[PDB]
Image 1 (cartoon, rainbow over the protein chains, first blue to last red):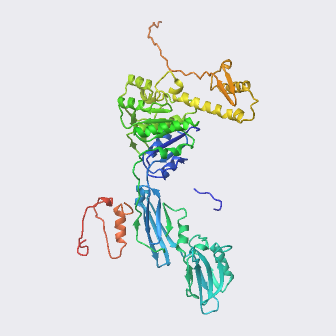
Image 2: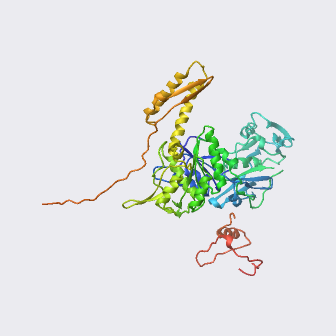
Image 3: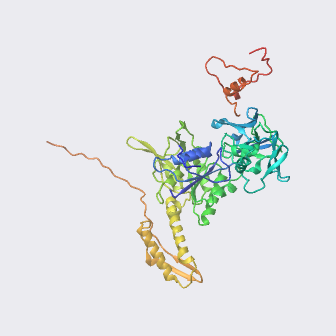
Length: 536
Length: 49
């Protein structure tokens, strides 16, 4: 590998169908060019590119995603080789592989075809690592290679003057573990010859050679053949397929790798949703309509948040859902840290397509916006990508479903432009006396404030250094820290007189009060027309 | 599903065989996806093209 030239803090999570990538592993997607290379097709791809494309400036942050399927690979066992596919799904059934042995080279030849990616390859001069020959005066020369009787790894290689062993190389271990040493040291017994292959690099570990005897030599040049040892080189980084040796290798006609399986749908998402526990997400969205999956996601979000690791979810159901379904689903999804989306629509992508967008894909579009906006700012009134909205929701309806905590888009009618902009960051929790639970952005600001508070209280006091730092110091420390957050305007002011501390044994109890940065809900303007005369 | 999904590959891979031949109709393009052929069986090639 000689030197050359060759030519957002809120993480967002996703889980859905995709025709690519191994399941039960959370991937981090560095660039949507790499997304398509992993997630070939399906709803997850549209969910990723919709999220990062949802607005020309409020783009989404670092995405984590997983294919939720019971998929398994396509494979075949033929000749001396088990052939297996790194793609899991029905797409693997399109793979084809076939061997030949070529009398022009006395080598094996391999061909791999994969029409889905318009991908095709041929490998020739497979095996036949390096040449041996004899030039000394004698009438006869040969050679041999032998195995360990147990492992069937190679153990000896020997040059022969006629029938008899001249010198041996210890393939069991040491300086001769790489065939390069033997390619050099045969040309330190210069009556014999060895010479390298022209067809690219090989550097085979000599233990991978295969047992051979008494090939007739002087004029002739003969290879050591070691076909599987060479195939490991020819398949180091190559294509979609991998190989395992059972038995002895032999060619075979072109045949499809079978057993490619997307697999049955999941009966429950819980044991595959758990992988997002410790991955640092904050917004997680399911790409599915079933209410049971939505209840499970609500449960997972609660399980992580109650453990100190805050998380929230945005959810939407099916297609063109009606009011009765939204109320019944809200009542079945009532806990905070969950948002329900009420509207479906159409989105445009660069392929020249107009999708019919389910409600959970509008949640993704919204979730990508929520992650793009810097901490504490509301999703209120932000412009969306929507090309046409699908609705039975008028003015008053938006009041109903806003007051009942369901998210909705509104169509807005400016001078020239119409555009779609979403109403307010309210969550599924209904009781609007408690804005800390109701408004998602208020909850986000709270979650990150309490986490930073909880963290710095560890270093200062929960480090356990002594009990002799009493409760008047803890009160002072919380006043100091509220001062620092007041300096950064994240809290407007705090009544230091109304802070109290109580201590018993090795436990402290503290009461406090904070003035939040007060929001601005409504304006109305009385515009009156009058006339007064111009004169000359 | 695989290599031969397009009739271009079938035409090339029949012609490769020395004993056989195959030729495409002249009325512009056809080159269908080979999955949509119809079921023809057991016609004598040595007798008919």
